[PDB]
Length: 461
Image (cartoon, rainbow, N blue to C red):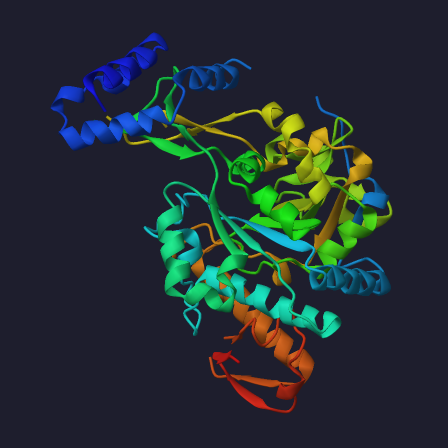
């Protein structure tokens, strides 16, 4: 940039009370000042102020979701579950199903230098989260082809952040997109925002670089428009979309039961939950808050509410729908994004941010559209945790939601699946890794009947 172009940008920022981002300019190399200029040119400081101000200067009625809006792998009629499976798989075979992967999180707790999806939890195959999820897509497409007699395609829209994009792109490239067509794996970005001080001033990571962060998982909706993803979906004739977070190592990607269930109810949004079994569990809950579908933090659930037993099933908690950030959307719902995306609030996330808790990241929440959605357009299905939810959150040596719990969940599932098919798993002081290319969800293991398998093992195609 010219001196005048630089001056004009400095004036814009200074007039907006953000002039301090230029404080170190004449300490900088000519390349470093150009980097700063280009980064600062990507933000409107005025909009930043408006967002910061709205966030810094902004008893509920709680009931479970309606009975007609809910189902359960555990408790629903097996006939309904089978029908939903078949109908969901028909939708897959029709090329009507897409997946949006939330892989734009920074994974601050796990503390890896690579994107979370690349992480190797210690399985015998050493496969990354990305590879396992990709292979589940590949297998499900093949299972769907048994219906159609033709290739089935589930496009995988991988939502990434500034700090995750390039290493994600390279990783997929290096692994030849895990046997999926390159045209069906679409890496895109969500928006970012500058991190801010308690007083709403832009934070500097270095003397020539603004500290930034993804705009929260709620940034997905806007990102679908800006990136051209929704348009791509339209051209493909996508009608049903599955969204989840890359950190769930057990994720049933594009789960036919989930798709079939939601499609049968003709909802705009559906959610997966696991069972809260003890009142004291600290889990966010999907429920009616003030008569609207919502996710309520466990801190907002009092002792009496948490302990309440289900009248119709007294062995079970009344409020038990533990959120696993696993959602269904209709394409029709995505068409409406322009009407309400601006209505999504930015929340203050107080964090320790190194710069030149002390700072704030402004974040939209994926579930903040839930209370905007008519009750009759919302559905929720309870699933089995041990088959469906194993988040990778913490480094080894935590004992909760870590590589070891993730590894154990996958390998115990594999052993379970084999045993149920008639396989004999023998352990000498555990579990078996079953490739998704062999089995998506426990099917297709009949060939292992009567066979002896020494755990730990790895069954691959």
